[PDB]
Length: 289
Ligand SMILES: CC(=O)NCC(=O)N1[C@@H]2CC[C@H]1c1ccc(Nc3ncc(C(F)(F)F)c(NC4CCC4)n3)cc12
Image 1 (cartoon, rainbow, N blue to C red):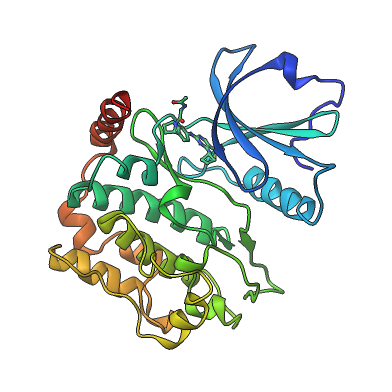
Image 2: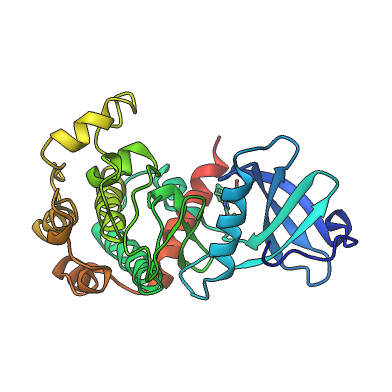
């Protein structure tokens, strides 16, 4: 396990575990304070006794995280054992997920473009490292209190090599999964680009396509239907960004690097600092109730 700490280190001493902020890839996630620096962190806690077929996946997740050095990937600080519980210390992103920031109401196209541009920067980094996220969706897109946008939850992240230029494993969240991943055909990083497209619709409309239906229906709906399109009063460049991602033929989908030059992004995206308005809005909203 990369970043595994000295097992004599007691994380209950080194860290103040605060409120739960979410349920994660495995186990729960908490807000916490690093007791040495007084920096806030995120703590993922997993019971190893309450495992197992997950520990390979937990190894794999932590391995992948430890191999990423990008402003666009959640930082991983190390892991601690406390009796049966694994404490995974993560970068704390105080804005929550893009999905949280949607709860007060719709995004405008500038905010959508900005968030998509930053996701594309993350996807470009990952894909350049032959890594595939495979669970891109709004809930896995996090923001710092400054409005920086980062990719999270590498629970099902894949790795490509010289040997394996392609993967076949059935992973992801159904609504966001690419048809070729659902069919377990040979696939690569283009799968993430399909997921990005679904996420673009999610960011624009609040939900992915087929969100009313039972997840098992999409197992045939997605491979046999025409891809979703963004329906509603949204700009033509936003609709074409979505369609460019959502092609059933993976070689017809652009790369992350290409989509960064897409007209929707260029014409509408602004500096990420402006996303603070979106976090302030969430605050005010969450005040009431
Ligand atoms: C009591 C209270 O108000 N707590 C804060 C809270 O509930 N928040 C804030 C704003 C929305 C929601 C929330 C969710 C997530 C975070 N931050 C965060 N940072 C890093 C991770 C990381 F573990 F990926 F690194 C992470 N993961 C959780 C698992 C579901 C998302 N969440 C912050 C918040």
